[PDB]
Image 1 (cartoon, rainbow, N blue to C red):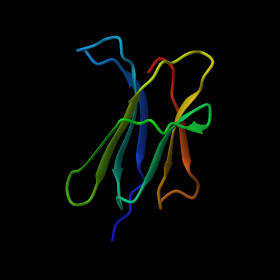
Image 2 (cartoon, rainbow, N blue to C red; image 1 turned 90 degrees about the vertical axis):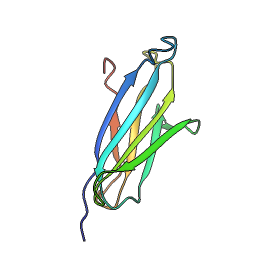
Image 3 (spheres, one colour; image 1 turned 180 degrees about the horizontal axis):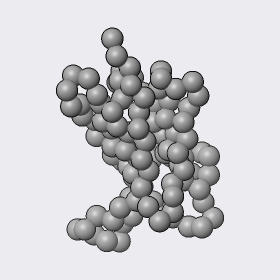
Length: 100
């Protein structure tokens, strides 16, 4: 058996087709087992309108999850990713660094 802690990256992107849109992205990588809970948070509250989630695996071993949604960042709001996994003793919260 193997278990691996997820690596978590939070960042923003503009689709080149559009430019108008800004997307908040949580990239959760290299984890095992695949059981996982992932949420985007605004000011601490769960964002239930998350339009996109892509899951893949490399070898039979490690899993990769891209979780993202459109958003409009202001200075007044905090955005974060929350991840719970069997390898974590407590949910991990990773805050969005505003120029990433």
